[PDB]
Amino acid sequence: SMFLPPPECPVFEPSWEEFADPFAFIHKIRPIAEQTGICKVRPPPDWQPPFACDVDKLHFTPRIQRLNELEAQTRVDYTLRTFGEMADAFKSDYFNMPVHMVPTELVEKEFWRLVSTIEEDVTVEYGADIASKEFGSGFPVRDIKLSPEEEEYLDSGWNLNNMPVMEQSVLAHITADICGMKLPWLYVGMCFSSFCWHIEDHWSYSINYLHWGEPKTWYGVPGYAAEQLENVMKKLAPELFVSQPDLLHQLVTIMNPNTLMTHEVPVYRTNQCAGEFVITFPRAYHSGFNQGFNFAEAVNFCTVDWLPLGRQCVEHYRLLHRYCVFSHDEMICKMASKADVLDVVVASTVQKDMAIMIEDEKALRETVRKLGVIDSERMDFELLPDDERQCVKCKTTCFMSAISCSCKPGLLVCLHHVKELCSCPPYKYKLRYRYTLDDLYPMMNALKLRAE
Ligand SMILES: O=C(O)CC[C@H](O)C(=O)O
Ligand SMILES: [Cl-]
Ligand SMILES: [Mn+2]
Ligand SMILES: [Zn+2]
Ligand SMILES: [Zn+2]
């Protein structure tokens, strides 16, 4: 009746030994956790990264949030103290109770009541920003003079600053600017502040640590059910599914998990408490809301497990005409070009993706030659700003190749949209390519040698 909580997602309590290597652990829980999309990880009892910051010197500008189910929201001044004061007073007055007296079950039930009730117009506020000098990681980082406890945690795989640039990770090697994606984000929550249903850019993993404060309630959907969810959502809120002019205009919304569950989309929940991690798996839809004043930190990452999905995702983006954050092929080639220093399991996995890339590229080039594109010239795509190498048609970031015509200087189409560049006959076109097929096979061989 009214709200029936989804079943609980998996909770893991790894031993210190399991905990020692986050990517090993994540790979271990994956068979379980990918069936639920999200999972919760409680570190060993004594893993306690020290949090320390001055609540008066940390400033941020909060996002205002209206709480209306199915209403469109776009995906992307207080001190921490003054936000906290506002946040505690709001929750306190909302329930006419002390903050720790309010049951999580009640806040949840009430959240889903208020977002579906037209007459209620509750607005809340929240902080979401990347780690910067004005607002840094809640984890220890090298710079100033650090206490021995902070140095214990400096190099932790679970220190979310390290997670991106570890070597079982794939996003580390990217030389392109993807700041929004490899740098941790800080989230300052208050009661009912929420994050709308979404999946990560390029279907990456995400990992979220709640440093302190009241819990964060999560809903997650396994990756296999992503399209199922999107279909449900498209029916109830087609506005969200219109073409978006860029990445800064992605539309997202609050939606009751019971709605999803009614439509046979599997949904799981959890209350993430302070000191606990939540991990989201590739293409796993998730949303939730904060129970009260709190402070979280999250970052995207990509394992070798993810590489084929990363390629599928970019294909999926092309079909949708969605902008890419980075070129997946450029990342693959960058890694190939560093085959000798790559981890060996990484090298082996990159090699397999590269082989598909090359075979696809071979077929695409044969096709455009048969269309009468004859002229060609090598081109260092990675030197162009992203906005100068997006396919006119499908907006994909070009790297392996593109078609240009002197008729339209600067414009490019990918080899899927040769027909979409201009009205000139194909013999006026140039195939611009990063590598000849003959360049590519030795790059792949280097990987094979490294993998042995
Ligand atoms: O905590 C928020 O406000 C959003 C969390 C984000 O979706 C994540 O992947 O950690
Ligand atoms: Cl409402
Ligand atoms: Mn997320
Ligand atoms: Zn295209
Ligand atoms: Zn032309």
Image (cartoon, rainbow, N blue to C red):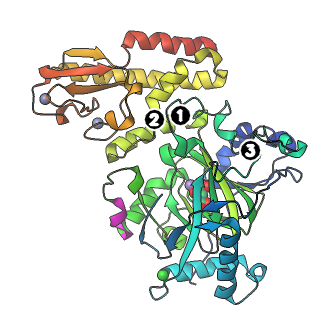
In the rendered structure, which segment of residues is drawn in magenta? 236-241
Residue 25 x %, y %:
74, 41
Nearest-to-viewer mark from 3 and 2:
3
Whether 305 is drawn above or below 195: the answer is above
In the rendered image, residue 152 lying in the magenta stretch gets the answer no
Mark-to-mark CA distance, 3 and 2: 28 Å
Mark-to-mark CA distance, 2 and 1: 6 Å
Residue 368 x %, y %:
22, 23
Marker disc for residue 351: none
Q: Residues within 10 Å of mark 1 (few under 14, many from 20)?
A: many
Dot placed on the residue nearer the N-terminal end, 3 or 2:
3
| C-beta proximity under 8 Å, tags 3 and 1 | no
In which image quadrant can residue 428 be found?
Answer: top left
Q: Residues within 10 Å of mark 2 (few under 14, many from 20)?
A: some
Q: Secondary structure at mark 2?
A: helix
Per the image, the residue denoted by label 2 is: 311
Whether 114 is drawn above or below 344: the answer is below
Q: Which is more toward the observer, 408 or 288?
A: 408
Residue shown at the point (49%, 13%) measured from the top left: 443
Q: Amino acid at mark 3?
A: Asn
Q: Residues within 10 Å of mark 3 (few under 14, many from 20)?
A: some
Q: Amino acid at mark 2?
A: Arg
Per the image, the residue denoted by label 3 is: 159
- Would the CB of label 2 be found within 8 Å of ligand 4? no
Residue shown at the point (37%, 29%) measured from the top left: 384
Q: Secondary structure at mark 1?
A: helix
Residue 77 x %, y %:
57, 67
| C-beta proximity under 8 Å, tags 2 and 1 | yes
Per the image, the residue denoted by label 1 is: 307
Q: Is residue 197 visible?
A: yes
Q: Main secondary structure of the magenta part?
A: helix
**Left or right for 417, reference 83:** left
